[PDB]
Length: 115
Length: 115
Length: 115
Length: 115
Image 1 (cartoon, each protein chain N blue to C red):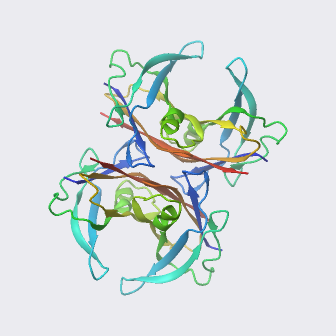
Image 2: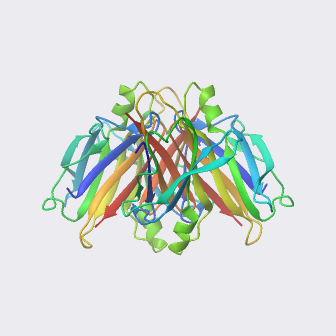
Image 3: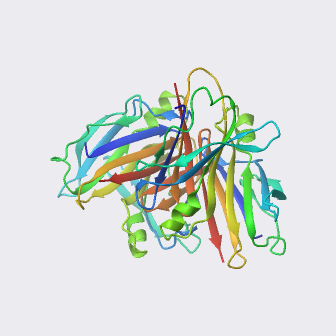
């Protein structure tokens, strides 16, 4: 599991469950190609998006569908989604955790990268 | 100006100066059209991006070039840039401040919407 | 004023108004002595807490009464308050801005120190 | 394990290892009584601070020794420590994760509370 996504809810103090996550990889023609997608679990985590074989060097975009999450809770939030864009595996394979802590008008996002 | 961008540096405890900022508006064909751009001032602020006349309801993207900022400081960053995507809605008079607090492997972003 | 406090609300996307703020300075006996206090304005800012003469090097604590703020909004909070503890150091001319971005179960706090 | 502390480093994109953490509980005389302490592991986590029996209702303070952490990395940080003050177990036993994401001039802290 070289790529994991974790989402937390700062209003409730809980994992953000059933959040849609779409991952894209930048192609040679400079366009965003769909790479993987899924929904966060009861722990606010999304595992099994990819494999070490498939997750080659490149520029990746993780789109976290925060608006649909807040709308289902009765909040009209500010952002359409939280977008995380980064170069992966350029010095060899790494394990990446992309995390976001969500509020209606804000989000904090960070990465934990391990060898 | 109805749209202001503010960028802060959490490593130095200072405004993030000379940061490139690009604003886009989503077109009918679903593509991102360049809308406005600039560089943050000595106060980490970017004023005068648009006018009330030009800034109509729509979906906007604010791209903050964080990678170039960290590279100029000799600090290895994670993100290619920080992206803020939101709908501008005419619910009475409004001013939008899009802010970001930057760290090499994280950023927090928020919006202050006032009348 | 060499010390300003700014508080923002991440649920509403607005300044956090009428928030009580208490500043303390650590005394020789290791206890926290009241130093200054006030309430944030309509811009979420608290100015005029001290003067350059009074604000000597020392360890200071800024306590932001977040619980009372959330309770007045009918939102169940986690923290009793947000506490910022720091040393003020005379390394040339300095102005300190202590800022906090509040959510019910989280807060981000940062400092902008300028000349 | 009803109380766990997790600390992350936003400069390195890694767990914050060997961070000292002190927990206090407010006593009847309004003073902070030492309750538990420890150091974060290689995963940036501190488990086994207390037991369900010992962790009774009360006001608790978790002091995360961020200054010593940054000083050991060659950074002179802004804060003396990150302080998290909260009421625990007032509606019955809960499991609490207190987390902090650290930068030299900023920190974000949140709680994940589960039943």
